Structure formats: structure tokens, C-alpha cells
View 1 (cartoon, each protein chain N blue to C red):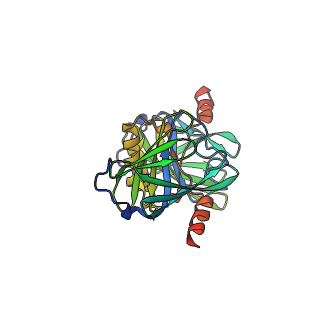
View 2 (cartoon, chains in turn green, orange):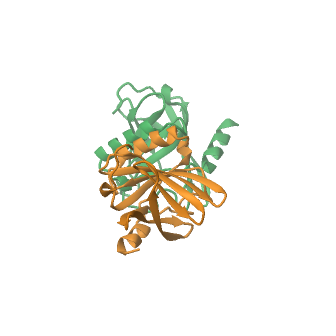
View 3 (cartoon, chains in turn brown, orange):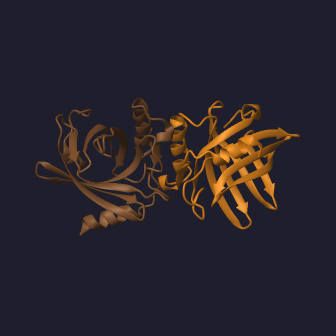
Length: 164
Length: 160
């Protein structure tokens, strides 16, 4: 795990996807016109159910997926018809944000994407500076980072689909 | 900023972010395109050429500024509506944060901008940008970080 005292209990509920880095591729992021993404993390007994929303162009897609633990505290695996994605929590304060490392094996590719999730839409200054230092350390350039626009069209469909 | 000398700020600057209400838305529308500035001294006034994307195209503006009481405050008098630009913070080497209040015929606009000497490694200047725009009353929702589309930048690099 890269955080070693991780408990998913401290991470359930709603998150906004504030930024991502991709290369490379374209545009992626987303486409146109960018729309913010978000995630609902759900504990469904030995499975993590994640529901994400992003703009796949003419629509807000809601994508629900299951993750299992992947051998290390904060290491999870998600298998999709493409291939495996391996997601790692890289840093968190356990209270406002979580920085995630994603290796994803689609059609014979291996790209890594990193993402900054936050509990809130304001006062992410400290989280984003952290995320710019860690993406850097992982080989990403300032051109690789995409800070999402505060257009919440998809977000609100995810909040609402989760409320009732 | 207190002791300011414009010889330090001559030249090409890239606009990394701006703040406005604001627107419508922003910037841008888508795709945004980056903005840029060229600062020249032309017969005792400040000659400023800026470019940015305004719905569908790169705009090239060319303005002239006068010093406006105290070291880092400049006034742009356009057809009697003003722009007041202040340098809020700078490290005198890689970035300058500018506060701009414009009266564009009736309307008041308060924009703040982050200009950089470089396109890379602006992490610290952006975090300072976030702290200085929240202090000035802007939300995180009000900050726009420019996409690295360099079409308007290259336009201004050529000539103007």
C-alpha cells in the first residue's frame, strides 16, 4: 500500500475529482467542454462499489464498478472487460483529500493516471500543491495535469442518483 | 509589492491563471488557450501587448500605462473608463501576480492574473495565487488555469 494505515471506512461517501494527470493522448480530459467528475464509494461486503460520473462527450456517464483488495492496505484491483486497473492510495490526510495512482491494462496498454479526489469544492490549495509535487515525482509534466472545471452537470446527476 | 523596478519585468510573460467573477464565460468557449503578455518601456510609459482567447479567437490588445502613485500601480486610461493594475506579489524572478480593476463603460471588473516567465514548474506561484485570490475574495470556483494551447502565445511571439 503507499498509505500503510488505511481504512476504507474513512473514505466512504462522496468525492469530487478535482484533478488528474494522464500522458500523450488528446483531449482525454473531456472533449469540447469539461465537466467535473465525482465518485461515490460504497462498502458492499468484501467489495468496494465505486460509482463515478465523467462526460463521455454527449452525456454524463454513470459508471459503477466493483473493486477488491489487492495485497497491501490501500491497494485495490478493478477488473473490467478491457483489463485490470490497479489503484493505489498514494497520500491522504484522512479528512479532505486522497491522491490515487491508477495503472490500467486496457487493450495491451499500461498507462498510469493519477487523480486527486476531494471531499469539497473549496480550499483545495494544499491538496493541489501536493498533487503537483507527487505527479512530478512520478514523471508527469505541468502539461499532463488537468484541473477540472467547476461545471457540475455530471456531478449533480451523480449526487441525485445517489440521494434517492 | 514595496520596492519595484520595472526593468526586472520587461519581456515576455505567459498568463498561467486568472481569477474573475465575470464573464460571458471565462477565457475560452471550449478549450482555453494560454494568454501572454509583452512588457515594453516606450517613451516613459509602459507599453503592454497582451493576447488571450475570447470566444473563438486570439485577441491581441496593445495598451499604454502611466505610473499611478506608488511603485507598482499603473493606470491604463481607455476611452474614459480606466483599468488600474497593481502588482500584488512577485518573486522578482519567475512570476508576478497582478490585480486589475476595470471600468469598462459602467461595468466594473476585478480580475487577478498570474503571469510567469516559464510554462513549467509554476506549482509554488499557483499555490500562492490560490492564497492571494481567496484573501481578495475569490472562490476556488473563480480560478481558471489556462490550458497549454500555445496558438495565441505563438501569435504574439512572432510580432503581434
